[PDB]
Length: 138
Length: 136
Ligand SMILES: [Cl-]
Ligand SMILES: [Cl-]
Image 1 (cartoon, each protein chain N blue to C red):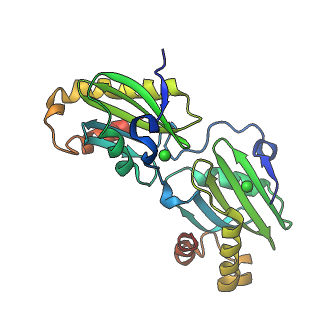
Image 2: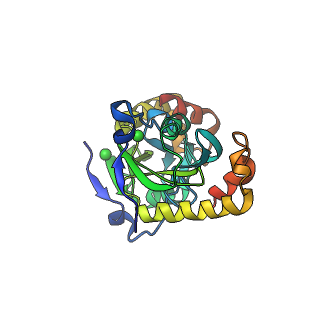
């Protein structure tokens, strides 16, 4: 029969320590994409983020919008603006990230650095430079 | 705030898919003697070791099986022959799956490293053992 569950404070009291995962932040994955073409990406841990992300990118409209899809323990957040998609994936267990505020800062720095060259580039054409920018916003 | 919809409304009935854990939603797993960790494996980054040692310092040596809860998480452990097998999941993880995983882990660690466990240094089974912890 399954073992008891007790509060950890019953062993260590009120100073029981707290887990801070993923640097204190909820975003595991972010991409800049145009339609199904990913221009830049960054993962904060290992996961099969790409495959499902492309599935979403292929189904969503290209009109301006903002939306969150939920699945299991994750939320997939995006802003689409001028056919360009800014997307990030959050882990529901982790400490609160302001997903839309991050995507907005990402978009701004992407629109500034590249602007409408995003409209044209090959898959991954900005990955080397912009990846570390994605890692640094956060 | 943008609206939140289920992903199945966009994609249809998906199936399994996202794994910080190339499979099972276990975030961390460890084998320890008192506070000496012998082998460990993490599925993402964070302060698992510092937190886990605080718990291990206080878990007694007697045979026992138990889950502690704290915040969003569950710490499940089996202590047998003074060795603790511990894993961390979230709150929504089916607890019987944690113990069946830890029981599998204990069996192999017993078979392989007999009672060298009582004297082995920190991390002395880590290269070999982490990639069996990894494979569930
Ligand atoms: Cl915690
Ligand atoms: Cl949200």
